[PDB]
Amino acid sequence: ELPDFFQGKHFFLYGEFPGDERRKLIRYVTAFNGELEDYMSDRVQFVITAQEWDPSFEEALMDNPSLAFVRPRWIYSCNEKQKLLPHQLYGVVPQ
Amino acid sequence: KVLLDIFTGVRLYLPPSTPDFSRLRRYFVAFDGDLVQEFDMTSATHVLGSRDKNPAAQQVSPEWIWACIRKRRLVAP
């Protein structure tokens, strides 16, 4: 009987993740009823990255104002506390 | 831990024609399952539905997936 606190939320995993982190993120987002996208689009609500901010982030922002850029630790800790934690705690911003 | 590692190491092709496909897939993947994509279908450890093609895999059932997750381990087909 699985929790559903990612339901309705569209995720895109951008870039390369270490080891099996990509598989783990897929597992957790799916488990909590998140919808993972094969491609970026203005329907994506959360980009999960380990990489740093690059101009394509800003380009995606100008086309989707509510988009948020978050680190994989958000997903991990959401699993650990079994709750929807505020993604702002793990955000990616320009460097 | 709520998400137990049950289907670790198993590669299952889940055809989209399967009833209750989305929930079945969600729970299977949530408990460490590994879905195989269509073109990579012939090389998979289990098949859900029928042994055609890839009879080298092992046939199981959605009932099998649910029974595995409720017994909290792997089990007979």
Image: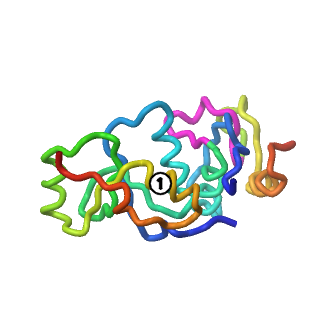
Which stretch appears magenta?
B34-49
Q: Is residue A20 above or below residue B69?
A: above
Q: Residue sitting at 65 percent across and 63 percent down?
A: B19
Q: Position of residue A27 (x, y in %)?
A: 55, 49
Q: In this view, does A59 lie to the left or right of B72?
A: left
Answer left or right for B20 relative to A83: right
Quarter location, residue B44: top right
Q: Which residue position holds label 1?
A: A75
Residue A49, position as x, y percentages in the image = 33, 46
Rendering coords of residue A66 (x, y %): 24, 69
Return the residue nearer the eye: B18 or A54.
Answer: A54
Identity of the residue furthest to the right in this view: B76
- The residue that appears at 29% across and 40% down in the rendered structure is A51
Quadrant placement of the C terminus of chain B: top right
Queried whether the magenta region covers residue B46, the answer comes back as yes
**Residue A9 at x, y percent in the picture:** 41, 66
Q: Residue at x 60, y 31 (%)?
A: B42
Q: How many marks?
A: 1
Residue density around tag 1, few if under 14, some if 14–19, many if 20 or more, within 10 Å: many
Q: Can you tell which quarter of the image residue A14 is in?
A: top left
Mark 1: amino acid = Ile
- Position of residue B21 relative to residue A54, above or below, is below
